[PDB]
Image: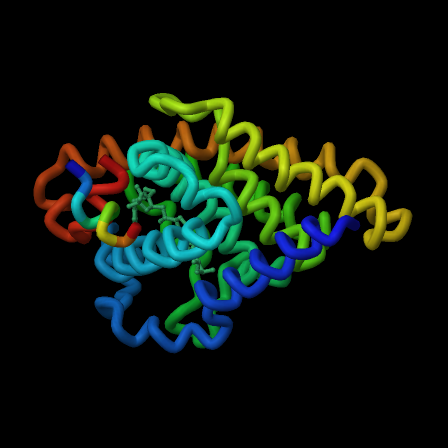
Length: 237
Length: 9
Ligand SMILES: C=C1/C(=C/C=C2/CCC[C@]3(C)[C@@H]([C@H](C)C[C@H]4C[C@@](C)(O)C(=O)N4CCCCc4ccccc4)CC[C@@H]23)C[C@@H](O)C[C@@H]1O
């Protein structure tokens, strides 16, 4: 509710609007989706690679992030990219058919698109439930962009050098979220909302750990790793 | 050793 806190919220909202296209116009640039085992890999690999760029673009605008060292910025983005991707995907996720609907039937993704290969259901079943539970929080867009930023600036990520500064930046955002809920999220929706949002960050860590397991299996098959992008291999590697 | 990500930064 402070002038500084409103400043943070305005920056994070504009940063999100600059890095998330609700028209999904750029999806034409991706390799084409095909729906028959790994038929969707080239299209979805380009989707993830595109989204990593947008997550980095959002991360740059977070107040205090640029004040970090270059190496802490890389550690934070490497460990959080897939978590922010899962978070930011909730905007396109719909509970009608439990799918990410990005504007066209070709750009609608369900469990069968992603969970037919290997053990990928061990990630997709918990991921859909996370999407369902996150949607049922009905967050304000202000709260959506704060949670993404809090997720990125995490002091406990492995390999963080300066950790006190990461904590100071995250607490600035965390105190902005808690004060926002009290001041503009009315009851009953705001009941326990901050604690439920923090719990979603814990769900993301287990989804992150499961994603790491499936990527390692996917990447060890060179024929499948050929289908990825250079940025995905660099970040998820 | 992360040229593309550091360039995006
Ligand atoms: C990222 C976003 C979006 C993400 C949408 C989804 C729904 C579909 C599945 C997505 C893309 C997830 C990925 C597939 C995770 C993928 C990505 C990858 C390669 O990093 C990986 O190891 N994954 C899990 C292993 C599955 C391998 C596989 C791929 C294709 C086919 C069969 C098997 C992560 C985020 C998910 C949609 C939209 O809101 C834009 C937003 O930016």
